[PDB]
Image (spheres, rainbow, N blue to C red):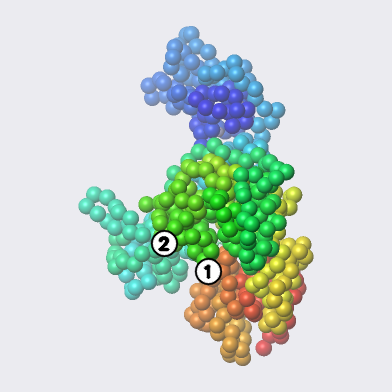
Amino acid sequence: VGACVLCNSQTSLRCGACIRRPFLCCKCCYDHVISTSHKLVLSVNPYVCNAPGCDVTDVTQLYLGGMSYYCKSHKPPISFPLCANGQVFGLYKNTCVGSDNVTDFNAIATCDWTNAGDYILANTCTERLKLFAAETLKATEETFKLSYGIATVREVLSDRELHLSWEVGKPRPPLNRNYVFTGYRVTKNSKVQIGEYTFEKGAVVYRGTTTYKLNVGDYFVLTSHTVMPLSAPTLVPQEHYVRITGLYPTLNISDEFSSNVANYQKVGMQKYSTLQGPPGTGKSHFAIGLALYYPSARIVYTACSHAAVDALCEKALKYLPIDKCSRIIPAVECFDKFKVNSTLEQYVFCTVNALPETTADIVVFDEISMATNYDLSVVNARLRAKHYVYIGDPAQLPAPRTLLTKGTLEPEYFNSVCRLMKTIGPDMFLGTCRRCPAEIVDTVSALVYDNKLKAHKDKSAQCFKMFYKGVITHDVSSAINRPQIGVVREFLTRNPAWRKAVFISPYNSQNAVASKILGLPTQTVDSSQGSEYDYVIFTQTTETAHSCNVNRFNVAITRAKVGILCIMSDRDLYDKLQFTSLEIP
Ligand SMILES: CC(=O)N1CCC[C@](O)(C(=O)O)C1
Ligand SMILES: [Zn+2]
Ligand SMILES: [Zn+2]
Ligand SMILES: [Zn+2]
């Protein structure tokens, strides 16, 4: 028994073809089964024919005869059909309201999540369907990981290098950081974990969580977890107040945080607030400063990634009493300078998926572009707070969508929070970039921030752009542009100071080739998000939707503190770069 995800109507029916098995009311369960291929219906029991060796599960072909269920062929003389009168049969038959359209729930229940349209709907549908879609997608995501073949260590060529043998008649996952494996040792009568791992083409390179002397017969699977059901909404109901509520501002504040005093008062004057923090505008400075402005306030700092939480811990270590901070870790190497797993500490730093059930004066949820509606609901379900602050930049990168192939996902569709920030705008905006030379601020201000991002620094005069298509080669799941690496190699012979540069590209294989030929440290745009370097060399590599995604480009070129060389493929973004042009040698 439970609640009808379309009506709320109390019901004893869940669709058994739906991977989540959502409770549906007589009217909603019926309208669902007759308009789609879903025909298995679950109650206190499953509406299946209880006859001996009969394979009827379709609820439109089944009858209640006695207190058992039968098809047409096996039914007793006295029966009624399970599924007639525009309704399906269970408990609470007389309480049931229905819907004028069931169209959105059917599409959510039946899509394979390969089309952008599927994510657009999951983000514009009613709130209760946002949860259903968030669960349904995540389960589809964790199941798709099972479809991948096991990889087995056939030979240990060296340290940090292997020869893999792959399961037959199953696809092989891409070998990039977005696919984290889990090793396993071959025991008497089972298997035991041996750290998480990643792989990249050579034989294969492997960068594992822990070090070992792993040997033949050891194997690797992408560990998938149980997806729990969602109760709480993605955003609580908004409330605007006329005074600061439940929070007592400080009388003395330092000139370090004085620029955020207006913004921190806004935080106290509404239930939830969005802060768009572009690159190097001071998001974590803002987050920690909130603690100093409201000194007695209990604050849970949360983000999706360990990295994101740890960076909040680093900043907190510089400004807040260590004895008042705690890092929550579930029983990967993260921050270890606070007492571990102390829920009742004033300042609690913890990933979304590890949150305890607790209350707080303020909740800060950082790197919000990376959040899914699933994460949004979980936080609302674990944390009951006087105030909620969402910090991020919908102009930066989202959580990768492993199933998406048709269409681009626009930032207004990354999650409920990014949708608000792109439709009504963000409550607060950090308008001054401290990190990047002016040529780079001017470029991304126009490109994705509506000319509202201002440069601290001056022109560096060390921002260059070269238009060079070169030659694109493809391997199993990535792109390589060797002539673009060549152009960079020639550039470093004539400009050897740039040998301190980080190499960035949109492709892990480009990076692996660039690492051999150049010896620069390498990052995917996607791994570079939240890091800064004095000097950045960027090869676009292709003109795909992937290498031209304006959020990706935004992150690529805002990594640079001093200078950047951009070797471009796309005539569009090249022409948008407010950088010095260089001829091809
Ligand atoms: C769609 C696409 O081409 N991608 C996103 C996933 C990683 C990637 O395959 C790579 O790093 O090679 C690039
Ligand atoms: Zn269904
Ligand atoms: Zn219903
Ligand atoms: Zn039967």
Vertically, is 276 above or below 10?
A: below
Q: Residue at x 54, y 16 (%)?
A: 81
Pointer 2 residue: 336
Q: Does the image show residue 419? A: no
Q: Residue at x 41, y 61 (%)?
A: 336
Say the numbered circle drawn on residue 572. none
First in sequence, mark 2 or 1: give its number.
2
Marks 2 and 1: which is nearer the front? 2
Q: What amino acid is labelled 2 in the image?
A: Asp
Q: What separation in Å lies between label 2 and label 1 (alpha carbons)?
A: 31 Å
Q: Is mark 1 on a helix, strand or loop?
A: helix
User: Does the residue tagged 2 have its C-beta within 8 Å of any atom of ligand 1?
Assistant: no
Query: Which amino acid lies under the numbered mark 1 shown in the image of this protein?
Result: Asn
Does dot 2 land on a helix, a strand or a loop? loop
Most distant residue in the top direction:
78
Image position, residue 42 (x, y; %): 48, 27
Tag 2: Cα neighbours inside 10 Å, few (<14), some, or many (≥20)? Answer: few
Residue annotated with mark 1: 508
Q: Is residue 401 above or below residue 62?
A: below
